[PDB]
Image (cartoon, rainbow over all chains, first blue to last red; front, side, top):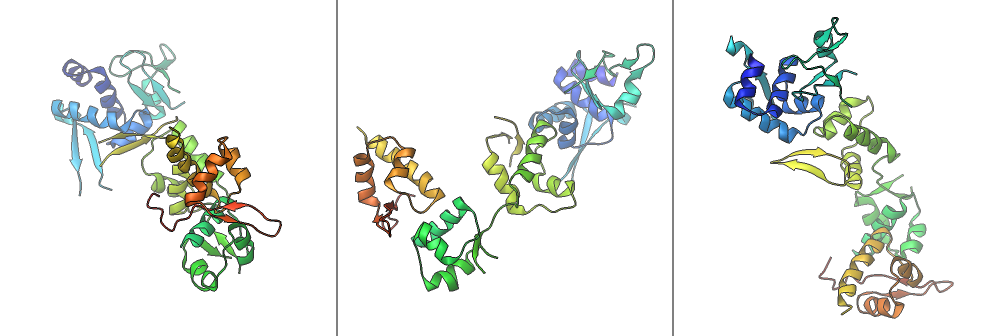
Length: 118
Length: 120
Length: 69
């Protein structure tokens, strides 16, 4: 999948970035960093790694704003985290990552059970 | 110059409203110049008839408190724009920068540079 | 020798003088338990003195020729 393809290409740390983006609308490093609670600095560099791969695309405008979007179309509480692919999700992702068969939120890329991240 | 700097430093340390005479004693400097030049043109000196110091905030705790919580959670960027967006009351440009420096500490920098604030 | 203390001690005075334009010998020792004779010789070269009503001893770093600030 998109999630898998990235993984083959790069590290896991990158994969987490791609996930949040898939999770919500186009975001900025600040936002991707805020929800995740990771340094913005590391976030930016993760973006570039994926971008070469084309997991995401960037638009730069003439502070200046950068927007990041996943090139998914190209291919074709409220703060949980995954213990396997170390990905992360918020409440908006809880109503979608939740499962009745288990009564919990399941990852979306590595289907690992996620857990609230303090 | 020296006397004025001492007056400013004194008021800044002590930080209260005060007649010209009250200032002389603690700093021991008197001139007419102070009355009709220094303590009127000097930005740090706020006339309230007596002379006071330009406090960053009415209470120091109000912006520093939010900055402590924001560090426990969220991202450092947009310090003045995120602080003003937060409440109807408007935060003073200088009180913001001031609280942050007194509070600091050090900030995780990454190359212009992205700056993130973390607890020491 | 103790010149390291001198240069380093001046830094302490600026911090002290940064909070108030005046400081008496008693307040300076609290900030530095170094011999008063040792502090006085430094204050004597760049410091000043002022006796007042009850004779309040106050010292001030003379900024007249302070090339270091």
